Length: 129
Ligand SMILES: [Cl-]
Ligand SMILES: [Co+2]
Image (tube, rainbow, N blue to C red; front, side):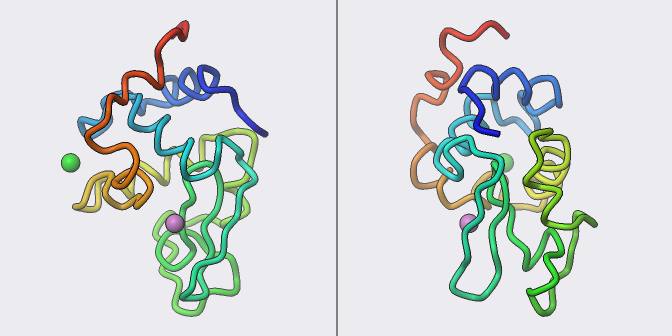
C-alpha cells in the first residue's frame, strides 16, 4: 500500500507514535517519506547483505528474520515479510523497540540527514487528526 501523507499520519497517531519517546508525529511521517516514499512494500538491500523492509525500512540484521541474513538477532520476533503489510501495526510495534534502543531516531539515517532539525510539523500540516 502507498499511503497518503495525512492517511499515514492518522494511522501512526492511532498506533501511538505521536510523541513516542518525545518524537512528535511529524518526525515519524518525515522518516517514512524518505525511507520508503510511504510504500509499505519497499525493500532495499544493504552492503552488509542485510535488507531493509517496509514503510520504516527496518533492517534484517537486528530486527526481523528474513531467512537470508546470517547472525540475525530478530529482536522484534517477526518475519521481515510482516513489515510489508498494508496494516502498519507490526512496523510500528517494531519501530517502538528501535527508538527505545539508546540512539532515538538517529537509528534511521534518513531521519538524521533529512528530518532532524527541520520544521517537521510541516509533514502533518493540513491533516484532520
Ligand atoms: Cl531521544
Ligand atoms: Co536503512
